[PDB]
Image (cartoon, rainbow, N blue to C red):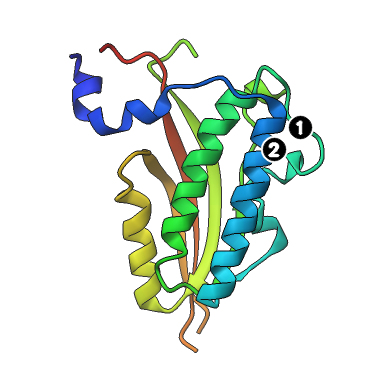
Amino acid sequence: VGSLETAYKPFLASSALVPTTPTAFQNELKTFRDSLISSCKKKNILITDTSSWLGFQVYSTQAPSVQAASTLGFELKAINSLVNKLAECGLSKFIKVYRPQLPIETDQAPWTPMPLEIAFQGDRESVLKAMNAITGMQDYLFTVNSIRIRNERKEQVFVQVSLNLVHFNQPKA
């Protein structure tokens, strides 16, 4: 294998893009959203309407283009998995999940970065667990572009992190 395939081996398999229709994406988005909302109710985590759409509120009514659905399904599955691990860290609020649109929504390099931002808040202990969860992901590689950590001084800490989800494009098998 080449050097990139070796170094990031466990992240390669989840980047395979599979056939996805626009309504199947939208139906998966809705399902993930309803499960996330239900999990935060049980865990006593506040979540704004905007956060609950996982960065894809632009597709709450309109389905995405046929050419984009499969790329979006990879991104949705990765973000869904990330936020769900964060919901297990004892945070008190999800403030925002903001996801800029990819060029395909309107891949020559070995990977394509996919930007997003997440804002949340909780006690110092839950934020440390959240930070470890972002970078300890098993199947999806999120890399940290930037982060802000701020005392609101309940002893709440506010975090806003800029991530690039790394989509591997053509690894050699």
**SS of the residue under disc 1:** loop
Residue 142 marker: none
Give how far across and how far down residue 132 sits, in percent.
31, 58
Q: Report the residue at 42% width, 22% height from top.
A: 16
Q: Please indicate whether residue 41 sits to the left or right of residue 30 in the image.
A: left
Residue at the spot 71% in from the left edge and 61% down from the top edge: 49
Image spot of residue 124 (x, y percent): 38, 77
Q: Amino acid at mark 2?
A: Gln
The residue singled out by tag 1 in the image is 63
Q: Residue at x 39, y 72 (%)?
A: 126
Residue closest to the eye, 43 or 117: 43
Residue 130 placement: quadrant: bottom left
Eyeballing the image, is 76 above or below 82? above
165 versus 93 height, above or below: above
Q: CA distance from mark 2 to mark 1?
A: 6 Å
Q: What is the quadrant of the C terminus in the image?
A: top left
For the N terminus, give its image quadrant.
top left
**Nearest the camera: 70 or 23?**
23
Q: Is residue 32 above or below residue 156?
A: above
Q: Please identify the residue farthest to the bottom as the structure is shown.
A: 154
Residue plotted at (35% across, 76% down): 125
Characterize the local packing of mark 2: few (<14), some (14-19) or many (20 or more) Cα atoms within 10 angstroms.
many
Few, some or many residues within 10 Å of mark 1 (<14, 14–19, 20+): some
Q: Are marks 2 and 1 in contact (CB under 8 Å)?
A: yes
Relative image position of residue 28 (x, y in whole percent): 62, 41
Is residue 45 visible in the rendered image? The answer is: no
Which residue is disc 2 drawn over?
26
Question: Which amino acid, mark 1?
Answer: Ala
Name which of mark 2 and mark 1 comes first in the sequence.
Answer: 2
Q: Nearer the viewer, residue 158 or 45?
A: 45
Total tally of numbered discs in the picture: 2
